[PDB]
Length: 215
Length: 215
Image (cartoon, rainbow over all chains, first blue to last red; front, side, top):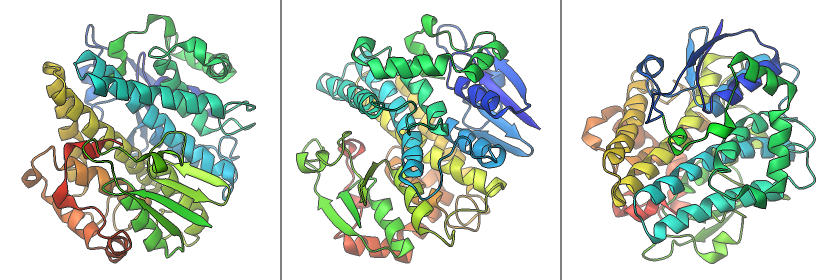
């Protein structure tokens, strides 16, 4: 019933982490990035009008967008609400907040990188400072907390994992001890280790390159 | 109980549209963009660690991020579920999908613009093509539909309004008749007209400039 189209070295990995955490059966189709550019190959691009991974098929539905896929999977398959806070609470509101932040952070990663590549001058420093602001905010928000919302592992942690992993390449990781602790907690989470097994090694965090911010 | 910190000519406007659609009482604090740069003024930046608008205070909660604020408001105040589809349906999944797309589209708007400003060469055409892909996808998806999910006006329409309004400045609006029709439907929606009244004219779509993509 469920098929995930998965691009190596991408935001697809957090979706496999979630699928494993939910204990779901699914078909996994794995695609390699094109050499040099890092772009999605034409066979993956064909799966969705935007041409990006991840793409989740569920019955007749074809979804893209990490946050959308996360919320879809939780809505249909997390019947115990293991990964969503109780509704009408500050925890629930913070949960949808950190989902939104995850997407904004990725955009910030992307933008500062591009501003550096091309020459933008002062604007390049403006965009670099934005990445710093997001990392500061997550770092401070993790103080005294196991997961981003608090004691409960939620859809937001699945979402946030990737832009933090990617973004650390553009900031000084030594400045963010809470984030470092948090990422180690994610990367050794048993469902995350299972995700690595299913994907022939999930993210190779050691083999990071600038082109990994695009598709 | 609720205070909205609102930046003129920004993604804050869709939040006022939603507040009016929900019939909520709230305090509205309006800030002008700084001249030349278009940046948020220091008084607004002080409201939240990321320094961007909109910022919603609700009791002891201080939220940022359009999608987060939308989902928070619907969770607490849309008890009739006027603006969310029934759960565990394709409509619900498409609703959270179009929320995610809204954020991605804004990022695409931003990125292509910056790639043009600086000189990025072929990469500039790559990013410009992405904006085209998002606009094509919304345009095609509106075919045969009143609102983005279908017959039901949802949180996704509130979200999408802004990146479409902004993005039209970087594409040829004549190529997107469904989007044009859809934006006219939004811009004459009675709650949107009320939003304009409360904000001394909401978005001045006629006074658009490149700096409006930043804060």
